[PDB]
Structure formats: C-alpha cells, structure tokens
Amino acid sequence: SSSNYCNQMMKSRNLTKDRCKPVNTFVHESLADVQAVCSQKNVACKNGQTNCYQSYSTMSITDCRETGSSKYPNCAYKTTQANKHIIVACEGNPYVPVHFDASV
Amino acid sequence: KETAAAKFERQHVDS
C-alpha cells in the first residue's frame, strides 16, 4: 500500500487490514448532513427496493478503486475526488443510511 | 458488535 489518501483510509478504517476491497467511497460531509439524505429524494435502489434516497445537492466524495496490479497484502488504490449526488439505502429508527447505493 | 448504521459510518464517512 502506497501513502495516498485511499491506501491510508482504507487501512485505518479496517477495510484492507485483512483483505483488499475492490472499491469504496468516502463522503467528506458532516455526519448529520449525510443522515439528512434519508428524508430527501426517494428513488428505487439498484436492487429494485424503494428505500433509497438521492441527495438534492452534490457532496464532496473520494472514490477509491483497486489498481490492476493490487494484490493482498499489498493493496493499491487509485484516488479520484469529485462532487456528486449520493444515493443511500436507509433503514431503522431513527431512519439512517445503512448502504451506499451509488453516486451521480 | 457493530450495527449496519455504525458500519456505514466507519466505511464511508470522513467529516
């Protein structure tokens, strides 16, 4: 693993300590603003479920994707920063995000 | 141990 943001965060957040996860997205917004998405635009999830919601506005996100030569234990990621709408699946009470469906 | 909500935060949130 290099020293770029993705390699470091994937490791510190216990995502690549025991394996190399292909892709992961990190959202750079306050926790409460992300939780607020669960009462925003209702949309169908990729699986057909209807408990997904899309944020009205774009949010700061970092996409982490394994490179072609990445192999455990030396996971390697390409870091891509962008501003896009997030789509999350919400459940429970309080109604909060439990899955990151996608980003637009 | 951790809930689905907690897992989401650990894996995706970086305030």
Image (cartoon, coloured by chain):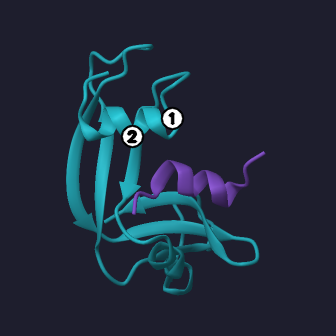
Mark 2 and mark 1 lie on one chain; the one further toward the N terminus is: 2
Indicate the position of residue A46 as horizontal and vertical percent values. Answer: 51, 59
**In the displayed structure, does residue A65 sit left or right of residue A4?**
right
Going by the numbered disc 2, the residue's amino acid type is Met
Going by the numbered disc 1, the residue's amino acid type is Leu
SS type, badge 2: helix
| Rendered image quadrant of residue A58 | bottom left
**In the displayed structure, does residue A73 sit left or right of residue A84?**
right
**In the displayed structure, does residue A77 sit left or right of residue A23?**
left
Please report the residue visible at 39 percent of the width from the left and 68 percent of the height from the top.
A86
Chain letter, purple in picture? B
Chain A shown in which color? cyan
Q: On screen, A82 above or below A30? A: above
Residue A15, disc:
1
Q: On screen, A9 above or below A36? A: above
Indicate the position of residue A2 as horizontal and vertical percent values. Answer: 25, 24
Residue A9, disc:
2
Q: Chain of mark 2?
A: A
Front tag of 2 and 1: 2
Please report the residue visible at 75 percent of the width from the left and 72 percent of the height from the top.
A92
Q: In the image shown, does A94 or A23 lie closer to the viewer?
A: A94
